[PDB]
Length: 29
Length: 29
Length: 29
Ligand SMILES: [Cl-]
Ligand SMILES: [Cl-]
Ligand SMILES: [Zn+2]
Ligand SMILES: [Zn+2]
Ligand SMILES: [Zn+2]
Image (cartoon, rainbow over all chains, first blue to last red; front, side, top):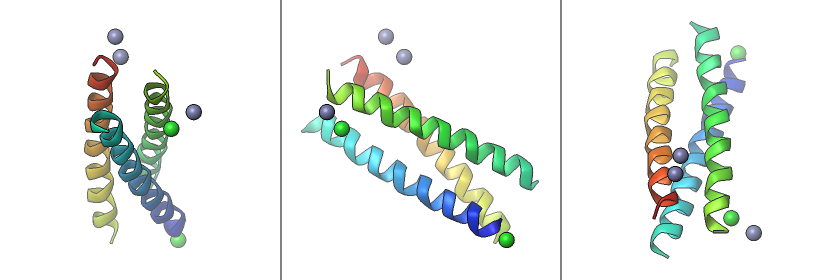
């Protein structure tokens, strides 16, 4: 269960970095 | 303690999925 | 380790809220 929590948090951190990147590309690109 | 953190993670997963769909909408007009 | 997991989730929640508000602005120009 701990590993599953850590993996889900890491996946969300990566998804948020990817979304902020795509937002910046849409706004400025 | 654990159950509340899992609930917060599930709500954050729902929120990120919604942001990804909204950002895809904006990329298409 | 548990406290680190909670502080990281709190930081992700703040970052996703910021993404949400920024996407709302872009949606409107
Ligand atoms: Cl475990
Ligand atoms: Cl896209
Ligand atoms: Zn497309
Ligand atoms: Zn709105
Ligand atoms: Zn509106």
